[PDB]
Image (cartoon, rainbow, N blue to C red; front, side, top):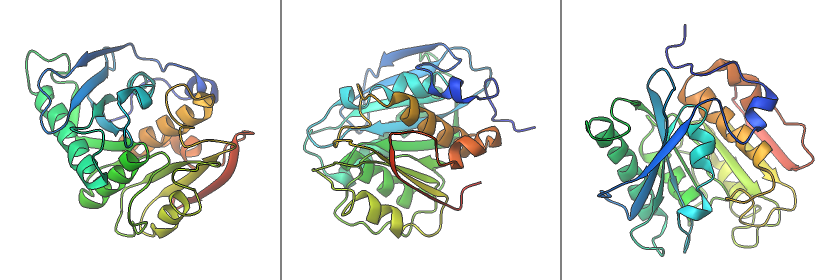
Length: 262
């Protein structure tokens, strides 16, 4: 049996729901180490240790922009840290360093007896997500740390679109009508550069640059795909293989690509 499988067998309905099967609590990180601020979301009743995911906002943005992922992922059996950066004007390399510092601190707290997440984390299984420059920072994190088990940036941007070095399973969310980081010059070239990995590209119809942020009108589809990708690749959970690899039946899909998915 897969030692990392958690929760009941998935269905479309269970993955499109606002909440997964586990109860979620959260806390503010008291002494952020290497980044500006953080909130940790965690399941109280997962029934084994779970992987950790670190999520970074874009330029000028704060945890509010990405917060919805915390409950959505934690409720399916993950510890999720959403961060504020040391400066709202930090660039991708700095955002990647701070994302990795946030994962380091989740590992520290997993060994801290006073922490709500004491003994809840499998510190060998980590993932990265983020918006825009925080998405570019996630891809830098993956390139630099190939032991990361999954990446799922949204509307990514970086100063270079060449992520051919990435060997981590990577799902790119893109927003059709993005005027900040146009799909044709940012997300799609980044996707096309990646030759060595399981990868997927999902572009949301009519979406502005914020189409995968807190308050979006496609949480059913976006949340299904993000949780399926992370379950498949962070937990090796092949119960999620079809949800992770499929072209989903949604009016909201305006571009779909996938390679090396199983």
